[PDB]
Image (cartoon, rainbow, N blue to C red):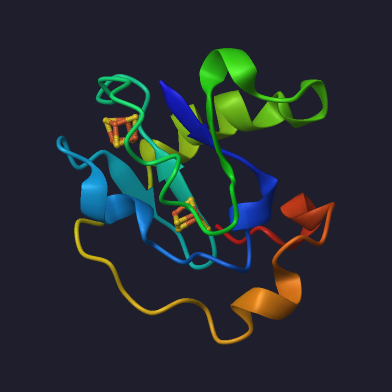
Length: 106
Ligand code: SF4
Ligand code: F3S
């Protein structure tokens, strides 16, 4: 499974959903997650993220390990997203800010 980590929060570019063959991204107010059962690990999404927020599960930084289980739980509750949309309004002021997990919205 590929995992969306911290820098997606409040950026949510959605470029990643274009390339997903199996449409396993699920959508929150300010973040996207990958559903781990559905991802086939084709890795096509991770060059597409402008925030470079997607990682193969086995490559998630030590300080972002929380996101692996977060993606699994929120994918069970959030709606499927299959079409790119606009980036959040202020997405490039927040691109690159560390510590955005405290802004995540359910
Ligand atoms: S690794 Fe492939 S299947 Fe998994 S989320 Fe990315 S594009 Fe979709
Ligand atoms: S910012 Fe998030 S919405 Fe996709 S393109 Fe990157 S994982």
